[PDB]
Image (cartoon, rainbow over all chains, first blue to last red):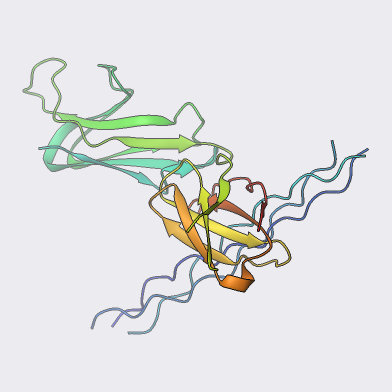
Length: 23
Length: 23
Length: 22
Length: 179
């Protein structure tokens, strides 16, 4: 038979790091 | 025949942006 | 049949919190 | 015979992507109408002599968001006379989803609820200390419950939600929750 449909979307990325301190 | 299994899930997403600074 | 090609990439993680103050 | 309305690639998108609204009727029709709420005039209309009509919105802007309805018409019909309206299609165009709240449900084992205001979203739990997310779940409801095991429960947690597939729209992260 034909090849299957594509898989589901990958897992979500890592959370963003907090920024530097302020001026 | 019927088509194959769904593919593996994709790669994980990228890391979110680093946060802004201070104030 | 053979399995499907891999799925699309995942979403990006949430944006970072702002940093501490000065 | 009520038509039905579909949105591709998604119902929630960022400004700048292309959205194709697709209306379909059981039997072929001459004119399809795209309506905003209460207005007798269709914003868009396509003459097609088909059972299907595609409405292409190139580079959507937050103005192109809103409640849409599909109606069709035949040449031999009266003036301003349209078919049954399709079920609504709410198209949301935004750079970012509204911030979710993360709370603990009272009942040992601990259950958290990441709550937003948008249906059909993927919810993601992050553990402060771990990079990759702890748990993630796709829900039709604008909230999702995560179960934390007994003595792995204490810590600092936050959540965000996003559209199930690309083009992704992301929410901000919730205020951290202290267990």
